[PDB]
Image (cartoon, rainbow, N blue to C red; front, side):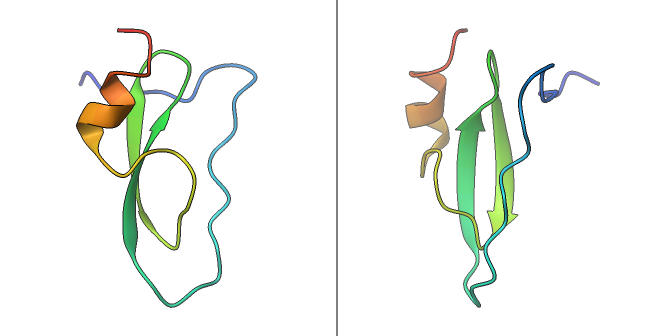
Length: 55
């Protein structure tokens, strides 16, 4: 398993209570982590997150 672990001092995104499902990609220090639900913040695409997250 190579996945993206939320680092020390970082938080999970806070899910909204909206009735929409979005897919968002958050830079968790050094890797991008994907969340689906009423999430905002982060990036809309994997490529955008990857280009803005240490590699």
